[PDB]
Image (cartoon, rainbow, N blue to C red):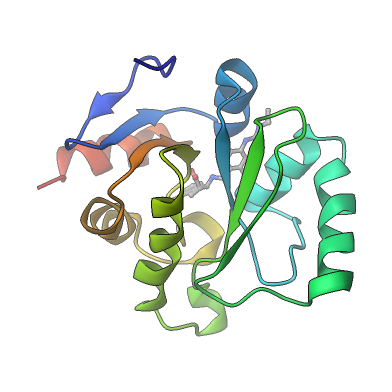
Amino acid sequence: VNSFSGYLKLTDNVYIKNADIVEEAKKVKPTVVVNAANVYLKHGGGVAGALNKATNNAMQVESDDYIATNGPLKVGGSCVLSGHNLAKHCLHVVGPNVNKGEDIQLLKSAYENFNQHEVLLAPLLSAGIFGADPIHSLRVCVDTVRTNVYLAVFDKNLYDKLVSSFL
Ligand SMILES: O=C(Nc1ccc(C(=O)N[C@@H]2c3cccc(O)c3C[C@@H]2C(=O)O)c(Cl)c1)NC1CC1
């Protein structure tokens, strides 16, 4: 049993809810919140901008030190950093950004990072300002992630379309 509340069950291991991932993280304080990161960990907008703002820019400060030491992530890759006031840990995962021409096949590799964590609160990778089709992202999620994932979808219209179109 866990504290995630009000989710629709899509599969054995994937759950979904119309929710602001920032508000959901503050309320549950999950072991892992996933950030929709880029390779430079520049958390300017979208989910990343929102999570970073909620940490009062502490996420960005930590991220800048990470990059200065380690260099950029790979598209499809991830790193574990602090969850600050939102979670124990933040898993920064880089999905391909279609508005940069990145290969959408890398979306499966991106979701594979979730399998290293038993339970996660997460957004749909490559959705929103990353330009991919969220219906496709949900399908890849369900077909790739085997651990327990609680997806937060900010837009109510999109959430309903995601639920109503789910096979
Ligand atoms: O600002 C926030 N939260 C907060 C949450 C999410 C997002 C976000 O980018 N959402 C994206 C979105 C929007 C439209 C269509 C989409 O396919 C997607 C994918 C992604 C998602 O829904 O995961 C943002 Cl900007 C802010 N909280 C402060 C108190 C105000």
